Amino acid sequence: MASGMGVDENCVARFNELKIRKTVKWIVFKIENTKIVVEKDGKGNADEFRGALPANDCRFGVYDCGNKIQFVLWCPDNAPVKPRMTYASSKDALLKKLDGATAVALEAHEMGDLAPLA
């Protein structure tokens, strides 16, 4: 349920360690139950998340690149579209607030999430 969501400032706070230090990162938060909170965040994003994410379920991770910033959502093959809707819908509330980043999101139904992005 994306309606009436509340966002924790920690999700946005990661951007001050991100943008100021100019070290690129990827943080993964969970959007359901009308709460936005991260379950994991790591430095070494492209290499780290390939082995750090055996998620099985869908979660929402934001990863920055030089060319663009895509909000990454891997779809759950073992889960329905109902939890899936929450992420793709509420991601605007994140995007609109945290950076001037790109309004495009990355949807993965293949192994793209844990695949070699870089």
Image: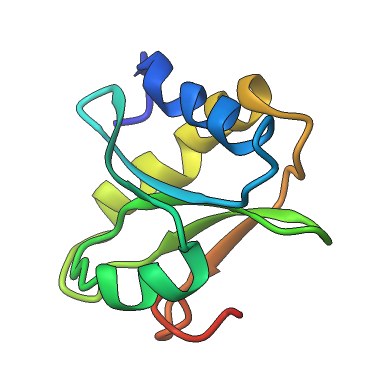
Q: Is residue 70 above or below residue 76?
A: above
Q: Nearer the viewer, residue 44 or 79?
A: 44
Q: Is residue 113 left or right of residue 83?
A: right
Left or right of 67, for residue 27: left
In the picture, the quarter occupied by the C terminus is bottom right
In this view, 106 is above or below 87? below
**Foreground of the two, 6 or 29:** 29
- Identify the residue at the far front of this view: 21
Which x, y percent locates residue 59?
Answer: 31, 53
For the point 24% across and 76% down, the residue is 77
Q: Quadrant of residue 98?
A: top right
Q: Residue sitting at 57 percent across and 79 percent down?
A: 117
Q: Is residue 33 left or right of residue 44?
A: left
In the rendered view, tell whether residue 91 sits above or below residue 98.
below
Residue extending farthest right: 67
Q: Is residue 51 left or right of residue 118?
A: left
- Image x and y of residue 43, in percent: 44, 54
Residue in view at x 51 percent, y 70 percent: 46
Question: Horizontal and vertical percent for residue 93?
Answer: 55, 24
> Percent x, y for residue 102?
76, 45
Numbered label tally = 0
For the N terminus, which image quadrant?
Answer: top left
Colour mode of the rendering: rainbow
Residue displayed at 48% across by 31% down = 14
Figure check: 59 above or below 3? below
